[PDB]
Image (cartoon, rainbow over all chains, first blue to last red; front, side, top):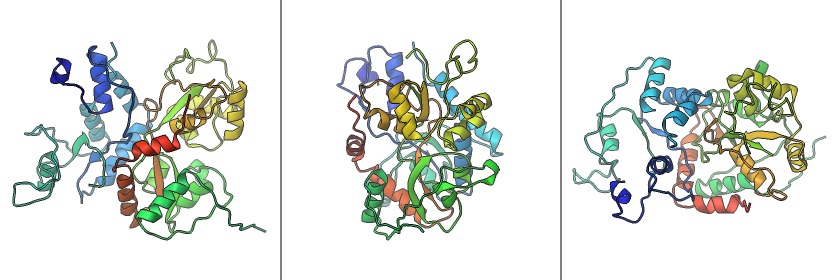
Length: 80
Length: 65
Length: 232
């Protein structure tokens, strides 16, 4: 990020949300609009964990209501 | 947002989360490592297999590997 | 008398089951029976394919619907191959669902036909989130998806709230590109399409691995260009 923001390299491939936040914060960095590899990145869990489904159900219940979306809009979506 | 998610999870469930920063700064690859020829991940995913980590809150890219 | 005609069809689920039978190499018995719609825990009334996949002894179903509460507590869905969520597509000045015109429909945005399909996941999600919006959609319940599309092409339907994938599929063949999706489906629900599997089934791991290989080999862009043909 420090290299691409100071005119050292050509481009940078990273997560869509991270690059969008960098473009909203840093005006010199303007990412492209073509988005690919649209897949929900899950939380890595153990192989034989007893609560493998409990944490997933909790995350699902938290995402069903209007809390995680509001937190994302208020924290990650820093528009200036 | 990660701290808020952890607080919400600890409020819903009854587990005690431990916040710690990884010593390295990379995720790791599944190539042949220089540790007794263990074709696994060398990083936070490898620490998860050993026992250091328990829940990788980072949104890792899901895949068959 | 039930006509058991052997009709062939093509589409998204057809290609999904074809690539599944080609990669996993399993035998299936596909049948299209006339059923109801998406069922939920309303008075424990289970109808349609959802009601069939809720009970055990069912292997799987190509229908990958939106993620919900009961459909995730009863059975264990696979990994969501798509990230399209529930959004609103008004047929310009609105800001999606966070606009103040929905909390107070008396002054602005008078009560119009804002209901979704009968017995849908959006109804349950709204009832869990907004009771008054759910009551409004119930008292202003519209007809099926085809009638909703006809009303959108006519102009009488104000807004149509559904999944972002359905909205993109509808907009891909608009008759002049009149209706526009105000806000993508990642700030309201952020759901996905999961294959209806069986609770504690040995094929769950195989289906998950097949999906992660299909969306982890570099053909996601090809699938997006082939299925989604939105020109406007």
